[PDB]
Image (cartoon, rainbow, N blue to C red; front, side):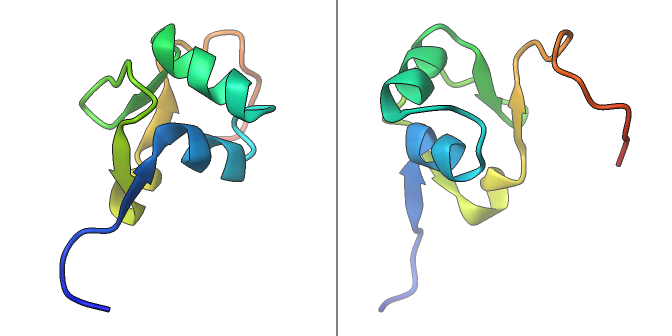
Length: 71
């Protein structure tokens, strides 16, 4: 309960955001450079992300990914 930085593995954040199927799926995707965080692309799953960055999570290439909505 101190002031600092609370980051979590990308794999965990992805699973929670229903971005991936299983832990192995999220981890594999990160290794294949499928998921990126903000202006910085992460390749390792051990990568820690902060609540602030959590919202700045996007897929390297979401061309196929559907979603007619914008915002």
